[PDB]
Image (cartoon, rainbow, N blue to C red):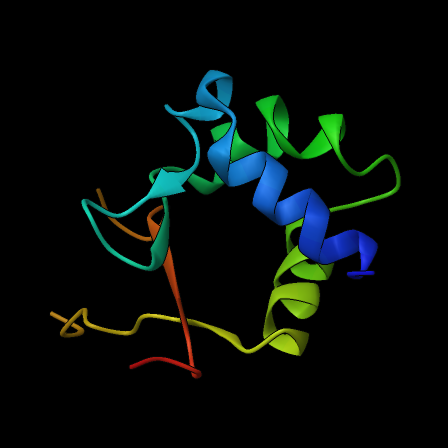
Length: 88
C-alpha cells in the first residue's frame, strides 16, 4: 500500500533500460539524472502520460526529495541530482 508515484519512481530508477537517463548514484541514496532533456524525452512518457519535468519535481519534493545545489554560480544546467531529507 504505497502511493502510485512512489512505485513509479522506484520502478523507473531500478529498471536497467533507463540507466543512461536516470540511475542511483554510485553506491548511494541520491538519484542522478545526467540530462534533463533526454530524461523527459525517453523515460518520463513511459510512466507518466500527462507530465512534464516541473510536475515530476513537484511530486518528488512531496516525497521529501530535494535538488542537490552544489554548483558554485561561476555537464551544466542539464544535470540534476536529488537527495531525500530523510537520511541516516
